[PDB]
Amino acid sequence: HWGYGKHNGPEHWHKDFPIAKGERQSPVDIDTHTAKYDPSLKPLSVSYDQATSLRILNNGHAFNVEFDDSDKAVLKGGPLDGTYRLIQFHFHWGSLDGQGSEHTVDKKKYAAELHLVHWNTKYGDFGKAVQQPDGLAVLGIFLKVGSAKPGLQKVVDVLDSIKTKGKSADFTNFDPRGLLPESLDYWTYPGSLTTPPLLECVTWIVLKEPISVSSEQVLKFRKLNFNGEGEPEELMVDNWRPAQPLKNRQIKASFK
Ligand SMILES: COc1cc2c(cc1O)CC[C@@H]1[C@@H]2CC[C@]2(C)[C@@H](OS(N)(=O)=O)CC[C@@H]12
Ligand SMILES: COc1cc2c(cc1O)CC[C@@H]1[C@@H]2CC[C@]2(C)[C@@H](OS(N)(=O)=O)CC[C@@H]12
Ligand SMILES: [Zn+2]
Ligand SMILES: [Zn+2]
Image 1 (cartoon, rainbow, N blue to C red):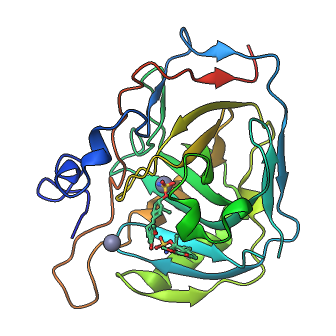
Image 2 (tube, rainbow, N blue to C red):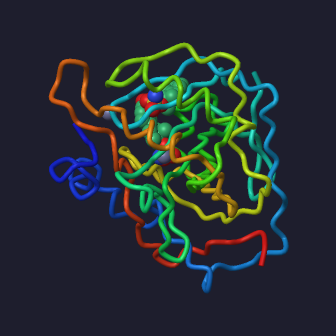
C-alpha cells in the first residue's frame, strides 16, 4: 500500500502509477524570477459561508475533513471557469518545522501545507471530475510557525481522538474561512493530485500569504500515526511529495 517511506514513498509511485513522470505533475517549486505576473488574473472567489463540515478522518496518509458538497461552499473566479465545490481539506507536514510543504517558493519549504480540494460541478461527481484536466481546483495554503491560528484549533484538538488509520470523529460546524490568510494573492498552474492516482486533473491555486500556526499546533500534527491501532507504530510525519519538474508550464502570479 502506497505511502511516504523509503519502500513505499514518492520514488516507488511511478510503478503502479506511470503518470508520476507526467507532463503536469504536482507539487512544483515556485521560482519567482520565472513566475509570470498576469494583470488579467481575476481575484479569487472563495464562498465558504455555507460549508457543511461532516467528519474528520485519519486515512493512513493524512487526516482529512469532509464536507457536504451540494451546503454550497464553492471556489470560483481567479483563473477558473464554472463552479468548484469544496469536498474536503487535508494537510501535508514535516518531521521538523523546516520542511513539510509540497509546493516550495524559491526552494523554501514551509512547516506545512493545507489543501482545500474542490471539484468542477459540470462533471456531476468527484469521481468523474478527476478524469478531466479541469476536473479539480485545489487551493494550497502554506503554514509557517508563529502565532496561533484560532480557526485551526478545533482541527488540532480533535487529532488526539483520530490517532491511528481509519479513526474518525464528528466535525460539524467547522468554518473553513478560519484557515485562510488575509491576502488572496495567488500563483496558479495546471497540475496533478500529489498522491496516487496522481491524475493530471488539477488547477492549482497556491496562496502567496502563509497562515501563522503555533508550534503547539503543528506539534499535534506530528502525533498522528500512519498505522492502524494495534499495528507497529509509524508516526505520521513527512507525508509530502517533493517538488516535481515544471516541464515548461507557466506559473502565473496575480501580483508583482
Ligand atoms: C471515485 O469516485 C468518487 C470518490 C469520492 C466521491 C465521489 C466519487 O464519485 C465523494 C467524496 C470523495 C470520494 C473519494 C475520497 C474522498 C476524496 C475523501 O478523501 S480521503 N478521506 O482522503 O480519502 C474525502 C471526500 C472523498
Ligand atoms: C479517484 O478517487 C479517489 C481519490 C482519492 C481518494 C479516494 C478516491 O476514491 C483518497 C485519497 C485522495 C484521492 C484524491 C486526491 C486527494 C484528496 C489528495 O489531494 S491533493 N494532495 O490535493 O492532490 C490527497 C488525498 C487524495
Ligand atoms: Zn491509502
Ligand atoms: Zn494534498
